[PDB]
Each structure stands twice: as C-alpha cells, then as structure tokens.
Image (cartoon, rainbow, N blue to C red; front, side, top):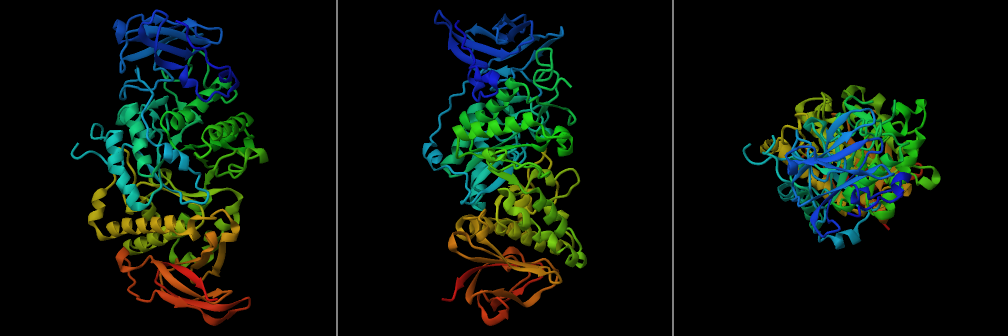
Length: 609
C-alpha cells in the first residue's frame, strides 16, 4: 500500500478537505486486493491499531506512523457498514478505544463504533447551485428545525423517528405552504446525548445515525433543492463533547483542546493548526459532500473572546481561525450563507475581513430579540415609558448585516414560548402574537424562526416530543399558521420588503414618537416600491390615527392582523384609503387609519402624481 499523504496545508491550518485522506476509505492495495484504508492524526501516540468485527474485536491491525504523526493502515475485504474503532496507545501510557474522529458513519447511540461508508452521493441539483445566492436582496425566511422532534412517525421517541428521506417528504410541503426559503438544521454531527440537541458533538464528520445513513441525508438535501428550498447546517466550532473516548486527550496529550469550559465540553485550541484544519474540514463537509447551502456557527462569542468576555481580551487565534474559515468557505462556495451571533457587539462580525471584520454574511440581532420580547412582556400601562424600546433597534441596525432570529434557545429551560412570554389574557397574547410577527416580517432584515413559532405553541420545546400538531384543531392556532404563511407570502413577493433591506434609503419612520398610543409606523421602500407598516401595541383601539406624509397618496390594505380570518376581533370593511390635504410642517398630508387594539396593518402606497 502506497498510503496517500495529507496536504501540507493541514499543518498550516488551511486544509478544508482533510476527510479525503483521514478517516476510512475504499481502495485497492498494491496487489489489487479490495479493502479499506484508514488514516488518523495522533502525533504523540506510540501505537495505534485498527480494531473491529473482522477479527472479533481482538488485537486488530497495527498502523504505521509517518513522521507527520498521521497513522495509516489497510484491511482487505471489509464491506460497507462494518464497524471499526482505533485503539490508541497514548503518550501518557493510556490505552483508549475510540471512534474514528473522522468517521462518516457511527452506530446508533449509545454505541460509538465507526462504520465504513462511501461518501459519493448522486445529486441532480446543479441548476439550483447555479442560481444560488446569499439573498442580500431576496427573501431569506429560515425555518430552524431539530430533525428528531418536528414530527414523529404515526404511533411509536426513537425508532418513531422518521428517516431523513421520510422527513423531507413530510417537511417540504409545510415549508412551501409557509413560504420558508431555507431550513436550518440543529447540528447533525454525531452526538451521544439527544438532549444536547446536537450542541455537544463527538463525530464532526458523521451525520447522525439517529435518522439514517449518509445517503439518506444527502437525499434530504437533494429533495429540498428540487423544490427550491435551501439547507443550512448548524455547526459547533467552539467546543466539543468531553467524552473521554471521543476527542479529549486524543493521543494521550491535550491535542484538540488547550493544555489548560462549558459543562461537559472542552474548548478547541485554535493555536493548534491541525485543529483549525479539522474544523475547516468539518464545516466544508456539509457544503461539499452533502451540498448544504450554508453554515450557522454556534456560540461564537465564546471563541472570539477569552472566557467569552471581551474584557478578558480578544482571542486573536480564534479571530484568525474564523476569518480564515469564512475566507475558505467563500472561496469554495461564494453563494453559501455563513452566519453567527455576538451579543457583545465588540467586533465587526459581518464586515469584510479586509476592513477588520470577521467576514460573516449575517449576524442574529440578539438586541432586537431581547428588546422586542421585553417590550411585549410589559404591562400595557407601563408601555408609554418603554416606547423607544422598540425604536432603538433601527438606531444600530445598519452597523451589521442583522438577521431577525427567534431561535430554539428562547423557548426552553423555563423561559416560556414566544406567545407565553407576552403580557395579558389569552386573547391579548394571541392578538399581540400576530402583531409581533407582523413587526418581525416588516422590520428590515432576514428572518429565522424555530419550529413551533408558526403554530403559536404554548408548551416549551422538548426534543423527546414532536410539535403539538393537534393545536391546529383549534381556531387560534390553525388561523395563526395561515397568518404566518401570509406574512411569508408578502415577504417573499413584495420588493418593498425583501429588496434593499440593508439600504438605509429603503426605510423611513412615519410615526416614532406616539408614546401614549403605543403606535409605530414606517415605510419600507425596496426597489422603489412603497409599503406602509403600522402597529398598535396598546390594548385600546385608535380611531382615525393620523400618519403624516410628505406627498398625497392612496393606501390599499395588504394585511390586517386583527381580521376575522386570523381569528382577530376586527370586522371593518374599508381597505382603500387616501390622504387628506394638511398635516404638519414638512409633511402636509394626513393618512388617517383606524387601528384595532393590539392590531397591525400593511398598506401598498401609491403616490398621487
């Protein structure tokens, strides 16, 4: 066997395809005998054996160590799906049997044995790829989903899980109906504990066997693309699960982790070049092998800053790693979408690396999420003083390419679901929920929502359960999901809303000082078209609320969040309005609008020439 040697870029932290050499791969030896070759980076190990069923889990096959610290070996005759592990004899005298860190397939948890798998999948999505776009000036309406707890098989937890293929068949119609453009999957890298949701990773290259085999996931992505839906993979580059037989103490030294923090994890050492290559290659896997359309990176602030705190200092190794990661991802897949968040606002997350940014495409607007939910949690009587809690977001909005996210992290651990966070009666919570999402879809910036948000779910998310689909037997919830679909439709089809979101010239306040009434109004002006958006956050109606315009115009209603069809309380009939002459200085025209309690309205504006 002439074993392939990994590119020198690996040791430079610049390798994005390390999994083409490392791991287990089909090949022929020098005598033309079919088998599998194995390669594992373990520079401090004194010995490594390939172990598996082939010799009844005995001594296995000794690997040979290159002066690079990469061990290689070959086993003839093995079939796809056969189990293997590495027995690692560590620098410290330890002996540990481990999953291949570059496993492509792993037995169903709790087992960690690696499985021989081919990684050459059939796709027919080349035209999808040619059309692909970061969506700066297109709708980006992301459905965040955990693959094990969206919908379960009829009857049945586990085994009652759909296979990836079956999941695609069930999910795609729901996405299309609600005009979600992309699904963002919680991490599918292999992980031992269902309740980590994928955020405590052991198998970075091993798409989780919970929902089937590698080809099954590839088929899921292929199916999405056929129907015009993108797939974003959640990724965990800050830390890994601390299991003693996974990545920690890998070669009997602190290899992947620092020589010297979140519970049950270890932090990756970005000053270790081969660790950078590992992570580069783990992100790239999703784009390359599985044809994903983007990467969302979890908890990046914990990497950017020592101990996650800018006051403790910037981790320049982390910054350089992330810059290089985004650079290489863009070099290979420029129309992929790469996102993160950083609520510290210390570094420029979405600015180009050239201008000292980190080079992400979008940043979740954590401030928008917190401030908006704080506001709608406030008793009506206290809202006048808290009025500018909502206007504040547009003061900083253009500082980053912000994405408005209501994610899985906000509907767990006693924090309450979105609707349950809101102040008031059942009916008032329901009315405000309609207005909240009106605001979400008509505030500039791309969108992300965790599964259940569109149902007006009351029960917090539990990965052991599916969504409460039975909620749609109730008028509120059924009408709410239709309302959510209508927001998606307007967002996807109206240039005023999706085009020029990041252009300050496309946003204009109309009413932003109406503290007593709790009324906010603004124009969205994408592509030279105009939509007026107006929301009432008080629990009383406003009659003929005046909105001052610089020009005379007609207004045709596109949406009324309190309409009967959304289970709302308004039964008004008038949809076509026009300004009257006279307003205020500089704005000599008034558009008078009736606002139902807690209600929002959207109008197409046609200037009178």
